[PDB]
Amino acid sequence: GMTIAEIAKDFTELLKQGDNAGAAEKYNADDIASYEAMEGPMAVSHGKEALRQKSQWWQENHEVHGGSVEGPYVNGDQFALRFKFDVTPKATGERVTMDEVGLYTVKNGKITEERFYY
Amino acid sequence: GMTIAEIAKDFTELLKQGDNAGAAEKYNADDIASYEAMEGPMAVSHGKEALRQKSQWWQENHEVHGGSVEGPYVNGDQFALRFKFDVTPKATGERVTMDEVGLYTVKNGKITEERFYY
Image 1: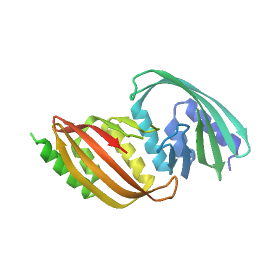
Image 2 (image 1 turned 30 degrees about the horizontal axis):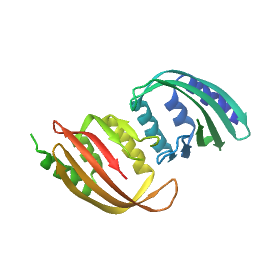
Image 3 (image 1 turned 45 degrees about the horizontal axis):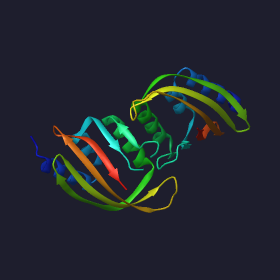
Image 4 (image 1 turned 120 degrees about the vertical axis):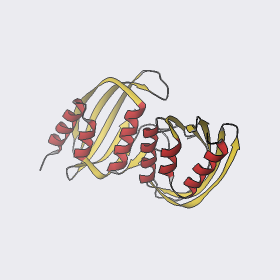
């Protein structure tokens, strides 16, 4: 029913409102594949509920001080967002600004893949 | 008042029996630190609930095909276990054998740190 442009707009709006979990629950495909930019073993994730667990883990391990979302930028079945996060990881305790691009693939109205570039 | 030997034996038996969640809830300190060997997205974790999420994430992304837990091996305030198990990560769909050593630090009856060696 909704077009990629509408899905992209709603999802981005939700993230700008800081409603990351609502955005994910609403739009992620049951089998969403998520690919972190950082090299390593748990970079790749499969499954909507797995991703929710990873997202909760990430919130428990970072203090988010602020941030912005720019986009959506659309091309065909995908949209890109540009994220800037002001965060203190518990792992380091050293405040940093993270700058990345997320690329979201949409099929049948659900995000089937998210890939982050850093 | 449980000795390290007692805690170690109970925790090990629980892991051998497959009660990973029970061992974690019974013994992990609220501020437990978990360190993978691999660098990567969930390589360093802090908090008991964070570890529960990481652990659920891991379970959802791997099929475990058996294996064994050897130990506990004790010295002072710590114990070590050796884990050898076949697993199929959802990311690759290719079955591999994992062989790792876990080192557990106990303070006031609770596991304050777990550290994995690969």
